[PDB]
Every structure is written in C-alpha cells, then in structure tokens.
Image: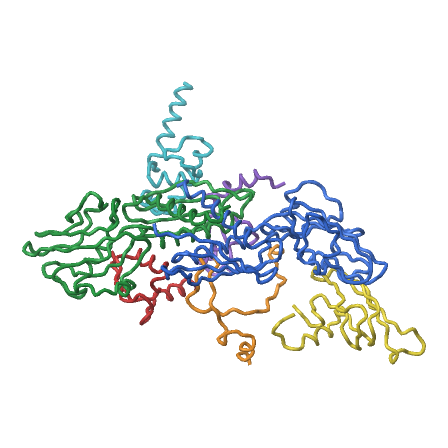
Chain colours: A red, B yellow, C blue, D green, E cyan, F orange, G purple
Amino acid sequence: QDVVLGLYYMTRDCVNAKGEGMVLTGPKEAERLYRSGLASLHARVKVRIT
Amino acid sequence: KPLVGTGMERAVAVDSGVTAVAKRGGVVQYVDASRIVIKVNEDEMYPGEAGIDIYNLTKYTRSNQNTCINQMPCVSLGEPVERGDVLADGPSTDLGELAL
Amino acid sequence: TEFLKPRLVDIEQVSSTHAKVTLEPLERGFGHTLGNALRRILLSSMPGCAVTEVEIDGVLHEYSTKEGVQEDILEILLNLKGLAVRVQGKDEVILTLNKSGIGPVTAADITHDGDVEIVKPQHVICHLTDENASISMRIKVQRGRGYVPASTRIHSEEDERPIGRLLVDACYSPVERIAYNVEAARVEQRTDLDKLVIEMETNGTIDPEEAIRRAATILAEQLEAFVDLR
Amino acid sequence: TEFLKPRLVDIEQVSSTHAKVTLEPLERGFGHTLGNALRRILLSSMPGCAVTEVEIDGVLHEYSTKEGVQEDILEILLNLKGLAVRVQGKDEVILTLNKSGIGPVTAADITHDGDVEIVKPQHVICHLTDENASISMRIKVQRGRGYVPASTRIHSEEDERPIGRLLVDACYSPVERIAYNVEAARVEQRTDLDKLVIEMETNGTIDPEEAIRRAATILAEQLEAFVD
Amino acid sequence: ARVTVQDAVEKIGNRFDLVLVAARRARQMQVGGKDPLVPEENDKTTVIALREIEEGLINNQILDVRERQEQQEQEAAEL
Amino acid sequence: EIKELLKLGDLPTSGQIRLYDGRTGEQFERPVTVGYMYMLKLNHLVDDKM
Amino acid sequence: REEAVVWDILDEVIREHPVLLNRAPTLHRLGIQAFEPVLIEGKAIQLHPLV
C-alpha cells in the first residue's frame, strides 16, 4: 500500500509543473535537479536513457 | 480531558461511583490527599446530629486487572460545594468528566 | 573567491523565554542548510540542569501520602520535574526546601545558594492545608544533556541507596521549541544575499547567544572528522 | 562536551569517480544532520568549470539542424554539457573546434592550450555523415559554483546576443550524484548510536574523496565565526 | 552462496540433495576438524560448505574415495 | 461550524497546513492534515505478551 | 547477570543461524518462513513489510 502509493505519486505528469521541456543527459542529473528543488517531480522532460 | 467529547462523560463519571460525590452541599473545611471534610450548610442540618460529613479517599489499590485506583481531591480549602457535586477525581476522571 | 561569511548581528529578546537571533549575510541555499543543522543540534544536544533525585522526610516511596499536603507525592515529583535551575560553578548541587504553614509552596521557598539561580520563583511545587503541617525536602540536581530515564542511572551506579532516595526522570535539555525562516538580506551591491532568523523558545538557564555558539562549536567539532580525515 | 568522535572506517572506490565512504560511530541524530549538510554543500556551492555558451555557424536556434551531422544539435548541447574541464591558470576560456572527415568527433580534436585539461578526450560529441561536411564552432567555458540552468540565464543577460548563440545548463559542481543513508551503530553499551554511509558520483577532474574534504573545509570555514 | 543457493543446484542436480550433501560435509568439517578447501573469510560452518559446493570442489562420487584411502592406509599402518 | 471555529482561532479553513521534514528540512509537496486526536492506551501491553 | 560478554557472544551466535516465524492460523505453506535474525533493543518482533 505505501510503496505503490509512492511510486504512483512520483510516476505522474502535470501540464505546467516546473522545468518542463528541459533536456537532461541522464537520470543522475535528474535526481540532482529534483533534490536541488529546481525541477518538480512530475515534469515532462527529455532524458537520455541507456 | 477529551477536547472533542459527547457530553455524557459528566454522567458516566458520577454514575460509575469511582468519584467522591458530595451527598449534602456545604463549604469545604479541610482537605488532604486522603481526607475531605465539609461543614454542611444550616439548611441541611438535621436538628439531632452534628451535620459534618467525612469523605475518606481510597489511595493506590490493586484492581482486578492489576491497575492502580486512587482518588485525588479536585477541590481546595474553603470553597463552596453543592449537593451531588464531585469532590475527588476517580482513576480516569478529570474534574468529574470521564477521561479514558 | 566570491564567498561571504555569516555574522551574528542582532539578538532580539522577546521575553525571558522567547528569543530572536538574526544571522546574515547568507548565500544561496545556505540559509536552510545552516538553519536545519542548527535546529537539529539545538533540540538534541544542549546541556542543562534538571532535578534528578528528591528526598523527603517521613516518606518511604512515591506511592504514599503525607498529612496536610493537598496533592500526592507523584504530583510533587512531577512538579519538581519542571524546575528551571541554573548552576554556575559546579555540576552537582544539593538543594534544601523547608516550609511550614498553610498556603501554596513555590520555588522561592528553596534556601537559595550563591551558585544556584532559580528562573521561576513563582512556580508552585506543593500545597499545605494544615498549619501544623511541615515539609522538609532535599533536592539533588546534576547537569547533563539529552533525556535520561530512571533505568540508566540505577543500572550505571552500583552503590546501594537508602530507602527514601526517590529517583525522578531527568529532562536535561532546556530547549523547548525552535524555528527558523529565511528572508532577503539588504546589500547595496548584492541584492541576492539571504538573512537567517532563528526563533528560540526555552526556559531560562540558557542564553540564546551562548546556545547558538555551543551548537556551532559542536557542529565544527563533528566536521573535524571530515576536514582532514578523508 | 563528552561527544564521541567517529573513526573513518574505509573508502570503497569502484572507479575513479564512484566512491562510498562509511562513518562510524555517530551520536544519535548526527548522521542525518551531517548527511544533509554535506549533500546541500555538494549540490549548491562546489566551484567548478563548465560550458555555458556555444556559438555554431549555420544554425539559427535550437530547432535548427546542421546538414551533414547524423545527430541533431540538442544532442550536441547535451554532449557539451557532459564535459569535465579543468582550468588552472586563468578563469575565462574560449575554445574553438574544427573537424572534418568520416567518423565520430571527440573532445580530443578541440584546440587546446596548456592551462586547459580534459579528463576524457575520447568523449564523443557527434558523428559525421560525409567528409565533405565540416564542423566548426566556438564554445564558452566559465568558472563558477553550483548549478545554473539556461532558463534563469536568458533574462540575466539582457544584451541582445547575435542570433545563433545557444545556452547550455552550467554544471559547475563536479558532483554527478550524492546520496546518504543512516543505519544503526553498534556499541555494546550504546545501542542508540547510528552510522553514516555516503555514496558519491563525480565527473573527472576531482578525486571523489577530495570533494568530501572540500565540503568539510568550506562548512568549517563558514562556521568559524562562532567557534570562539 | 550466502543469501541464495541458485548455482549450487546445477553442480548438484537437485535441491533436496544439496541439504544432505552440505550437512554431510559440515559434519566432519566441524567435528572432524579438517581444513575446508574453500577459504574462511569469517563465515559459519554451515555456509562454508554451501560456498564450497557453489564453487563445486566436492562431489558425491569423489566424496567416497578420500575416506577409503585413509582407512586403507590406516590398516596398512596397523599391519 | 468547524470552519467558523477554525476561522475564529486564526486557522486554515481547509484544515491542513504545510509541514517541514525534521530530517532534511524542506516543505512537503502537499498540505498535510494535522490536528489533535484523542488516543487511548489499551490493556494489550507488550511486556505482558513477551 | 547479563554481562557484556554474553552479548559479545550472542551477536556471533545468532549470525547465519536462521529462525522460523509463524503466524497462526497458517492457512498455506507461506505461513512458515525462515529469517536471518538481527538483534534489536526492544520487545517486539520486527517484520519485513514485503512478507
């Protein structure tokens, strides 16, 4: 119940949340961006994924 | 005391008998942690006897479920009391209101 | 470099309990970092003095009562638990309280000592109802930090204690509640610096400036294991 | 005053960028305080050098595409962002790159001087489709601290730059990733204590262990106004 | 190995036999005192056997030859 | 009536406020309902069942 | 007497020594599972939420 709620909450999208549309070079800087507060957790972004 | 109650705590506490309720109204004359005395008013004085009541509190006593029972005086020296009024809080009462 | 250094500039004293401390200048993001670190340190590791052991004549245990005392011995110990006492010189103080008569007993009735400061002399501690009733009490106060239940002290100390050595739990920490907020500092050529205002509420026995200084010293001491030890 | 000083156990380095450092034992609640302080310092105020502005001939803006390169210019911006460069002598570096021929281009091909070092000359920027096409551009490398994206720099520079300049998010901080966990410490008289385990990912140009020391030094030198 | 037992079964061929062979090993590994062929690396007696069959040094076919050579040389010493 | 009483006490009508984590110290994404609730200590102790 | 030595022996006695956990009623085969013990200061059994 708690794990699924957290994962569902953070695998979401919002129309104009924060830092939308910005392009990132990996998941590491995505995490650093979220931790620094410059990007929201639900933001449609372009990520280079291997 | 429960901040959000129902209003019948005042009823269940005095109907449970675990609190010391004043039989006859009067003015408190002397209290301890164990004894409470009240000088009954002249209108409840029977013409034959002294007309002074004694309320002997029950201190820490074992329960059937091994829990403490005590009564602590909720009144002070020299303040008026009425008939059917609480004097000592029960094991789980606060100023005559049940507080679980 | 372009780095700037925080400075303690104002100590606003709302009352003897509530205090305001302002720290500025602060760079971007440092306000919340320093504020949260200071809050976690101040709420957990501030030394203070607290009542730890009470001795009363004619009383064997804390589950008994004495004639003339309105409340119970447990209520007496719980009232003692909230005693705000400051000791300058030593770390262990024996306090003596003697009272006889009818009326409330306050902390002002403790026989005052040259090296003991009582923050609240009007803090009621016991009630007497009989004129012939008298109460003599010996209070032992140590100094420490954190919260110490009644099990650790008896486990640590192996000597026998006589019957009547009533043990009370010690809440050494004097800090009750603190909070902080970050605003914008005012610099003519730098309109981006931040200023940290930390609100502190506690009993006496702690000057806010010395508390913040102690917190900074302990944080630096903890970081000393990181500055050069890899 | 009787606080316990941790003994740094060991540092596990999977690579020259991946590191994990464990601290034991720590006073209760100090693990979280130290971990947060270090993480905020690492993500906020680590000086470094990174590219911010790239000017490419033949392109007008981000959506515009140069002919002859298999990739778009957005991937070019990403690849430039993922560059670790050390500048020792001076503080402002302008670099120009000119390449042609069949094959991928790399950071080794950029015109370099003595006071600029690149830890990954094999880092790939783009692949060329034909030898006829030539790639030429000038890039701007600045020295700074923290992380500033392009969205907050367009308004900062109110000068109308010549059209064709491209803004790149500046990752001055060498820390790629910092994470920390707090677990229970073991003292057979003191079960209350806790321990820190810190996992750090950096780019090149900085020893991952050295980043911890730099953060500790900056925090201590910022707190030394209140030590005595 | 230490948390899972996946690669033991391929060396063994069955799951219910791995417990039997591991207990048979740990018997004279603990009370026989013979040095384990897998290293120690601060492990317990019931898991070093599991690691040994992880790296598969011993097998039931070879588990019954070194214990007969020892007794035959014992009887040669007696006689 | 609850809304009027909260207005009287200078409290939010919605009944939820923003809290900051005690560990990292940043505001949670969404307002969290916090109030005073009457808890009970039940006779099922743990040392009696140990 | 619970001297320090008994705990210094316990922390290595339990290690790599699995312990079964049972929750009545055991409706199916999964009601009995074996876990590797970890020593905790307390009075209650700590159970992994996934099980």
Q: In the figure, is residue C172 to the left or right of A18?
A: right
Please give the name of the residue rendered at 70% of the width and 40% of the height, measured from the top-left corner. Answer: C159
Taking depth in this image into account, of B88 and B70 the one nearest to the observer is B88
Taking depth in this image into account, of B24 and F21 the one nearest to the observer is F21
Q: Quadrant of the N terminus of chain D?
A: top right
Say if residue D109 shows up in the picture: yes
- In percent of width and height, residue B93 lies at 70, 69
Is E55 drawn above or below residue A31 in the view shown? above
Q: In the figure, is residue A30 to the left or right of B43?
A: left
Taking depth in this image into account, of D125 and E46 the one nearest to the observer is D125
- Which residue is farthest front? C188
- In percent of width and height, residue D65 lies at 14, 63
Count up the numbered dots. 0
- In percent of width and height, residue D204 lies at 27, 46
- In percent of width and height, residue E3 lies at 40, 47
- Which residue is farthest right? B48
Say if residue E22 shows up in the picture: no
- Which residue is farthest top? E79
Q: In the figure, is residue E51 to the left or right of D156?
A: right
Taking depth in this image into account, of C17 and D134 the one nearest to the observer is C17
Please give the name of the residue rendered at 60% of the width and 52% of the height, measured from the top-left corner. Answer: C147
Quarter of the image for residue C80 reads: bottom right
